[PDB]
Amino acid sequence: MFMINILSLIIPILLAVAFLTLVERKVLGYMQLRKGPNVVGPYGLLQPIADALKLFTKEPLRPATSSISMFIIAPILALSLALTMWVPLPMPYPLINMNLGVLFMLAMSSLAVYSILWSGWASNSKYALIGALRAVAQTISYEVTLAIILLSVLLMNGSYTLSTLITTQEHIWMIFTSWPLAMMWFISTLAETNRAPFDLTEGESELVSGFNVEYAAGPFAMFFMAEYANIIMMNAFTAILFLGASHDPHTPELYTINFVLKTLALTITFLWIRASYPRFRYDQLMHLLWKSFLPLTLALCMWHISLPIMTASIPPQS
Amino acid sequence: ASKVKQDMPPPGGYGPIDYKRNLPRRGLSGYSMFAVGIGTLLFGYWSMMKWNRERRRLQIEDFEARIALMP
């Protein structure tokens, strides 16, 4: 019966990712004065299915100069970790209830980079290596700031339990308390998910395909699914963190609908941003994160440590 | 005895065509934006202060229940 719950979490996530791709194409098209997919199915509703069936019936290629074990392990690790990040999210009840769910997401997101690193290295081609090294620089840029931002925000929660965040925001959204932290958190999520204007690893105009340039068919499809599931997952995490829906224990579906609407709004904002800005330079991303976000984040961390003691606002939990 | 017919501009002239850059100002002032931000922050701080104090009292009550039940 817990297996049924695992499947009821996994399969709908994959369906949402498949249709997220259709949504991105349609939103970008209408923002570019065109229509996007509207032939394959009514309103392009069958386009993701055609894409998936096409990618899983095409020839997967193993490069001659590549290391096979890492080459094959990396997409598996990417997709499995993308699916694993969803299990502690309370919607309003989590599949897995963790004391330190935030730390769990931090650690698994840190482990997810090695899929790109090992993929790029094991492809044994120059563009894949350049993409992998860009991933190294990107993680170095965003990780410290993202962790300190999370700590500063959760000083209002009293713990790292994700369900407590619902109780914390019972009367007001936490974005009214820490919008300067929310802005930097949103930009750091853009960097962490390798999304434009921070999509350095793929580097399409610049590096052709970046890290997965040598990937074809099903393995490439798995990388794509992992990336889009990560987009949805990070936006759901932000929605839980900063825009807390009210939860009625006798009618949890109201919370579920509200939370899903907020997650969709944030994902559509991601797609909106991709159609508006040019790409960063990756050293410029490092300098943005280390010379602007880091000092402000340190100062705001001190402020959010002092404020509950200043005003006698310390949250309950031990 | 037909007259010459040829693609020509209309009598007098065509309507004037704009070419200069048109980028409106379209914003508030810096002082107003900062003031709105700080006002929102203060409202949030006050709300959170009240709610966290209530949460502390509720936790004390929950702990007293356990203390009563422990023997």
Image (tube, coloured by chain):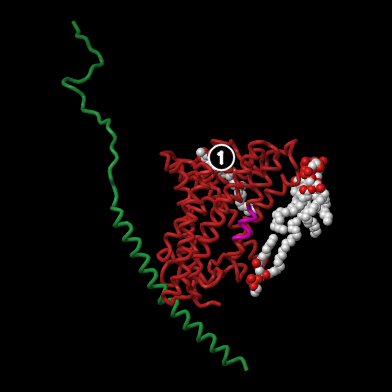
Chain colours: A red, B green
Q: Position of residue A135 (x, y in %)?
A: 60, 46
Mark 1 is on which residue type? Answer: Gly
Q: Is residue A265 left or right of residue A203?
A: left
Q: Position of residue A86 (x, y in %)?
A: 59, 61
Q: Residue at x 66, y 41 (%)?
A: A217
Is A196 magenta? The answer is no
Q: Residue at x 61, y 56 (%)?
A: A109
- Dominant SS type (magenta): helix
Residue B41 visible? The answer is: yes
The quarter in which the C terminus of chain A is drawn is bottom right
Q: Which residue is mark 1?
A: A203
Does A264 sit above or below residue A46? below
The quarter in which the N terminus of chain A is drawn is bottom right
Does A114 sit above or below residue A306? above
> What are the residue bounds of the magenta stretch?
A106-112
What residue occupies the far left of the structure in this picture? B12
What residue occupies the far top of the structure in this picture? B1
Does A199 sit above or below residue A172? above
Q: Secondary structure at mark 1?
A: loop
